[PDB]
Image (cartoon, rainbow, N blue to C red; front, side):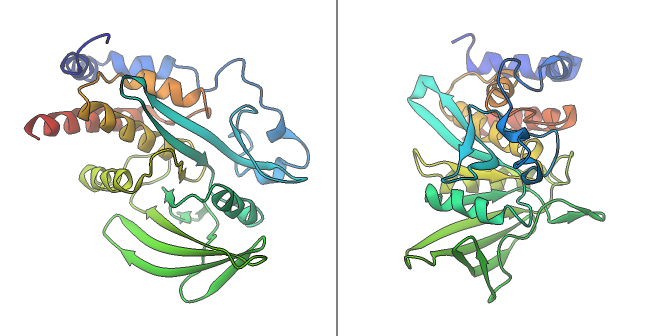
Length: 283
């Protein structure tokens, strides 16, 4: 629309070399002015936030059934209008010991079939996420759900697990694929860009149309934003549609604040976009 895909990529490359592109990223607002954040700060919800200042907007937050409706999680939907396509996500923080029940409730309510976890449980002494699933063959109970891990297979950059969730009240069962990317430091970039691109292609292969993919990290913003940005760009490149990563980031941030944390994360994702564009031309 504004340019060809070819043209947008020339602009991106030029902008990375110069490098105006990183400047513009830093000028972008982190939170959208004018979206209320109030439920996240209610006294009863404060201990449900892993990070005090990483909070969902009222309008896009995920609602739970009942008295305590709050979870730190956001609907993030990425539109490719020129293609009649919307990639749905739920972006959320790493569950705390006492929010595991709410996490699984969200998976259950929406019968989500894919969880993408972009963090290790700990990093140099520092807790990043609670282990909300059991080591096989142990079983785990969270808020009336029985969780078991049916399989656990490792690769160099990520672990793949099949999980069986049983509603203990009704006996109803739900299977979820759980992918944990372990080779990606908080506030940093993937250790290996090729392993990252293989992982993103794998996530795309598991996506079901009109069903959200649950993506989380520790805060649910930095690494989560990079993944969403990459999947979006991959859809655009295949469709010969122009890619403006600053606009992709802004559109994410209008749904969950602070997505893509660092200029180095942004730089990485832009370089990876150029790489997949170039490979797409070779087919």
